[PDB]
Amino acid sequence: QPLPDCCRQKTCSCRLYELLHGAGNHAAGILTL
Image (cartoon, rainbow, N blue to C red):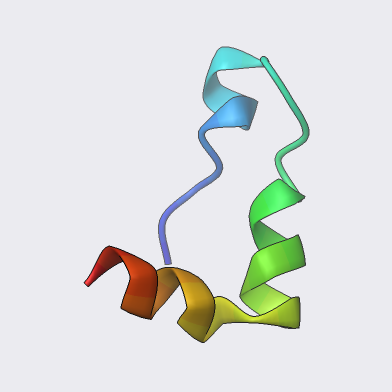
């Protein structure tokens, strides 16, 4: 999977993606399409 954006710009937590990727990864996969 893709790396964290906030981690690249250091504008927020990197594990932020894991939050949704674990509590609902499909939510982002479908909403994005």
